[PDB]
Amino acid sequence: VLSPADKTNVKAAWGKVGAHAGEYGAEALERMFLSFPTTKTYFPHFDLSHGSAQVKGHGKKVADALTNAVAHVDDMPNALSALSDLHAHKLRVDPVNFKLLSHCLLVTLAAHLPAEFTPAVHASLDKFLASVSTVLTSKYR
Amino acid sequence: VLSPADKTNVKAAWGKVGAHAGEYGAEALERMFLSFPTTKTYFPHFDLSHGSAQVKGHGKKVADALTNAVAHVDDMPNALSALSDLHAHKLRVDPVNFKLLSHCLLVTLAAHLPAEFTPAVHASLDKFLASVSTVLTSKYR
Amino acid sequence: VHLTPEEKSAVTALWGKVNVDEVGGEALGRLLVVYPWTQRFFESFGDLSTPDAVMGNPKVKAHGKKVLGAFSDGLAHLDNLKGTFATLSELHCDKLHVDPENFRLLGNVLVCVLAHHFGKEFTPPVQAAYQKVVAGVANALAHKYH
Amino acid sequence: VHLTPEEKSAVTALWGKVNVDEVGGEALGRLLVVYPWTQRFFESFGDLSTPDAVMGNPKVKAHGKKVLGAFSDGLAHLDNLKGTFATLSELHCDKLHVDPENFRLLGNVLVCVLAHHFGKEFTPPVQAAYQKVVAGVANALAHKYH
Ligand code: HEM
Ligand code: HEM
Ligand code: HEM
Ligand code: HEM
Ligand SMILES: COC(=O)c1cccnc1COc1cccc(O)c1C
Ligand SMILES: COC(=O)c1cccnc1COc1cccc(O)c1C
């Protein structure tokens, strides 16, 4: 659950990502795969080589989902229901893996947006990604 | 995020507690204090001796809060806002302790309501307590 | 782990009554249902699609029996859990790459199952002693992470 | 205690450019702001009500420097992290009873701080190397729980 200030910070910071959605998405994925190689087993038939077109494409999907989450922060379980079906029912992703990707998303944002990654915004983003992770790891249909 | 089935499972199961609120609430607290001594550091001013009147009375408060939480499962942050301010803002309880208490609540329910504590209901109760725990440990106001 | 002589007697007395055909299967089964992501480690176990299917699954009951056997061995060697589970830790950490968190969950699910089976006989002091046991087992299964 | 030779080279090269007077305070300060329950361990530190209060708190910055000094000591003994943080493990586990998950959180906050300061130079391979560092530190600090 997010405070009004959290919603304000998340919308402000993620809005500055903009056209760098796919890039940041892909970078976060590649950081996760390289830092926590066990996460690669969730993508057995993917081309996970460095600079992979598939990873580029998939990072774009992740980022755009987050943009959607941000726009529907007051109705996230409804908006992310299909993504919840995928991650919670079909894939059954271990929630520890969501912590890893959320962390890598933070690392990526901090690496690219130093002026916006303040302690307050950091905290808000962390709570937001925790909210997303719970929604996607939970079966509520 | 709870499913319509989770909500149904929780209301039926917790509804069987009834007049056993103070008893089960108290028992759950004593199980936590005994099994995980570090949780006692949040209650230094308390009489935490076995069978204490203070712990038993507090157990009734906790059980009643859960009963209220069950009834307001669709607007928990508003309903639990006062308890959130207490646990998140003032007390600043580490979330790990909420996991310990939630686990002891399940143990109590299993010990007392074996017919209710089916695998599916076990899953729903655990997700319910996790949600209550997240709300009480989050600063969202 | 450090159990008082009074705790060890209560642990031993309760464990002697444990249904070795069912308790392990129910613990492993509840794990798979309450924490569905754990099912990913058991793809070759057949049908895990529903709670009833997980609990009744013969491979789940069979493997759960082996799990309960490990806890039995741990109780028989409380002074050397790291050595007793040395082989099992190599398997769960190097090969299976199971997250240490999952070790604590199963330990606590086992506790719930004991509570479920023995009701009022599973008193808070009895739970407290069993929590020391499952914490020690969970930790001994993860030293090879350390 | 691990890390490939290349990972050790990467970690050592970057740490040489780390401001030992600032990074520790940033990391500790962000820990307290992002995970506010951690403030409970620092009630003698004074004002921790707002993010600006925390980051500007002299005692936070001072203690953060000690924290980072311990990380430096870890990096100078990468193949012996358990011994390096042995005494600190006793303090944090036996005396302070800090739940080990918080150790991992601080480690990852430090990674965010490193990323924040170095930006593009904090490459995925550099991060992966440091992830093994902070995991080793967290593990070593929780050794008395093991
Ligand atoms: C903020 C967190 C996450 C978001 C927003 C997210 C979003 C998405 C999206 C948008 C898709 C594609 C859906 C489609 O193709 O229709 C997807 C697929 C997938 N995700 Fe995630 N995801 C997240 C976390 C994770 C994590 C942590 C893992 C595993 C470690 C994971 C594993 C997968 C897998 C295996 C697929 C299917 C890929 C395929 O086979 O095509 N996700 N996710
Ligand atoms: C998990 C579900 C929990 C629920 C439903 C809950 C509910 C409550 C309730 C109803 C009160 C009484 C407040 C009042 O009447 O004004 C309370 C107080 C309190 N709670 Fe909790 N609580 C939970 C978890 C925890 C945990 C895990 C801890 C610590 C380990 C904790 C620590 C405290 C403390 C220290 C008080 C103040 C008691 C006093 O000084 O009077 N709570 N909580
Ligand atoms: C926490 C206490 C645990 C105990 C006491 C335990 C015990 C055992 C035992 C005795 C075996 C048999 C190994 C052999 O015969 O060579 C085994 C194998 C296995 N364990 Fe566990 N285990 C635990 C936790 C876990 C958890 C949490 C998971 C996954 C979430 C897991 C996944 C597996 C898998 C996938 C196998 C092999 C299955 C197969 O052979 O097809 N274990 N475990
Ligand atoms: C994860 C890596 C960590 C490292 C390397 C580290 C390092 C240190 C060091 C060097 C000291 C000084 C000890 C002394 O001078 O006696 C210290 C003290 C302390 N640490 Fe940590 N620490 C870590 C994590 C944590 C965490 C996560 C918490 C709490 C959430 C924590 C809470 C404390 C407290 C309360 C003190 C004593 C404060 C005081 O003296 O007033 N530490 N730590
Ligand atoms: C902000 O959350 C939501 O959008 C929303 C709206 C209606 C029902 N459930 C939710 C989900 O909230 C969660 C879920 C998990 C963790 C968390 O910290 C929050 C706020
Ligand atoms: C449980 O409460 C609700 O579902 C609800 C209703 C209205 C607004 N926000 C919520 C928040 O949900 C949460 C919050 C935290 C964890 C979690 O797993 C859920 C579903």
Image: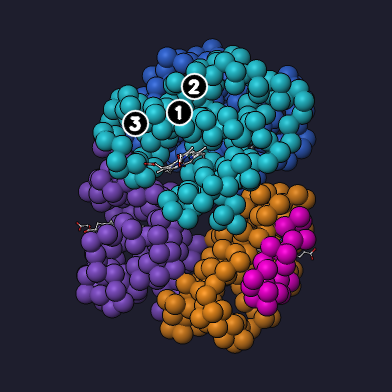
Chain colours: A purple, B blue, C cyan, D orange
* Image coordinates for residue C121, horizontal then vertical, percent: 61, 14
Dot 2 corresponds to which residue? Answer: C20
Dot 1 corresponds to which residue? Answer: C65
Q: Are marks 2 and 1 in contact (CB under 8 Å)?
A: yes
Q: How crowded is mark 2: few (under 14 residues within 10 Å), some or many (20 or more)?
A: some
The three-letter amino acid code for the residue at tag 3 is Lys
Nearer-N-terminus badge (3/1): 3
What's the residue at 29%, 69% (across, down)? A48
What's the residue at 34%, 31% (across, down)? C59
Q: Which residues lie in the magenta part?
A: D65-91
Near-viewer residue (C91 or D36): C91
Q: Residues at marks 3 and 1, common chain?
A: yes
Q: Could you say whether the residue bearing mark 1 is in a helix, strand or loop?
A: helix
What's the residue at 44%, 80% (across, down)? D123
Q: Is residue A69 left or right of residue C98?
A: left
What's the residue at 51%, 30% (across, down)? C68
Dot 3 corresponds to which residue? Answer: C59
Chain letter for mark 3: C
The residue at label 3 has a CB less than 8 Å from ligand 3? no
Q: Do the residues labelled 3 and 1 touch (CB within 8 Å)?
A: no
Chain letter for mark 1: C
The residue at label 1 has a CB less than 8 Å from ligand 3? no
Chain letter for mark 2: C
Magenta span includes C24: no
Q: Residues within 10 Å of mark 1 (few under 14, many from 20)?
A: many
Q: Can residue D50 be seen in this view?
A: no
The three-letter amino acid code for the residue at tag 1 is Lys
Q: Residues within 10 Å of mark 3 (few under 14, many from 20)?
A: some
